[PDB]
Length: 147
Ligand SMILES: CC(=O)N[C@H]1[C@H](O[C@H]2[C@@H](O)[C@H](O)[C@@H](CO)O[C@@H]2O)O[C@H](CO)[C@@H](O[C@@H]2O[C@H](CO)[C@H](O)[C@H](O)[C@H]2O)[C@@H]1O
Ligand SMILES: [Ca+2]
Image 1 (cartoon, rainbow, N blue to C red):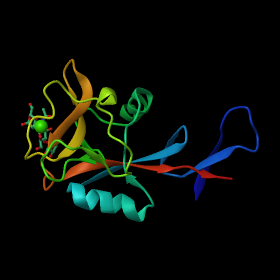
Image 2 (image 1 turned 30 degrees about the vertical axis):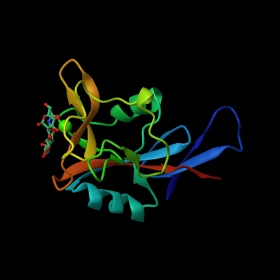
Image 3 (image 1 turned 45 degrees about the vertical axis):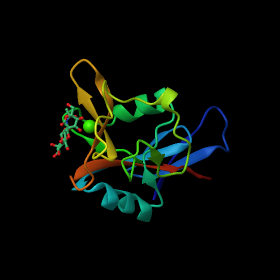
C-alpha cells in the first residue's frame, strides 16, 4: 500500500512511499521507534529495502528533524567500524567532511564507532558518535517508487 503524491505541477509524475513512510524529494523516510543495536537496526532497514539514513545536504538534514523528538537519539547510517576516523555511509557514498553536522567536539572517541543524531540545548540538532551495542532508535531511507 503506497501513498502517492504529485511532484511539481507535472501530472504523470507520481512518487510513492509505503504509508507509514514520509516523503522528501527523491526519497522516503521511516522512523523506527524500537530500541536496537546499530547492527540490528541496519538489518531492520535491509528487509524494508532500505538503509539507515544518509545525510548529504543541509536541507535533507533539516527535513529529517521535523520528524524527530528532541528527547530522543536516532541512529544514522554512518560508522567507523575500526576506530580509525575513516567514516563510512551504509550506501557507499563518499564522506565529505565539509558537509557534515557533528556537534562541537564530536566525534570524540575512537571506541564510539556509530553515529546518532540528537538534540542539545542551543547547538540544536547534530551528530555524535556512541557505542553500537547500546540500543537506540533509527531512521531509514529509501528511494521513492514511481508510477
Ligand atoms: C549528550 C549526549 O549526546 N548524550 C548521549 C551519550 O553521548 C556520550 C558521548 O558519545 C558524547 O560524546 C558525550 C559528549 O557530551 O556525551 C556522552 O558521554 O551517549 C549515550 C549513549 O551512549 C546517549 O544515551 C542515549 O540517549 C537516548 C535519549 O537521548 C536514550 O535515553 C538512550 O537509551 C540512551 O542510551 C546520550 O544521548
Ligand atoms: Ca561521542
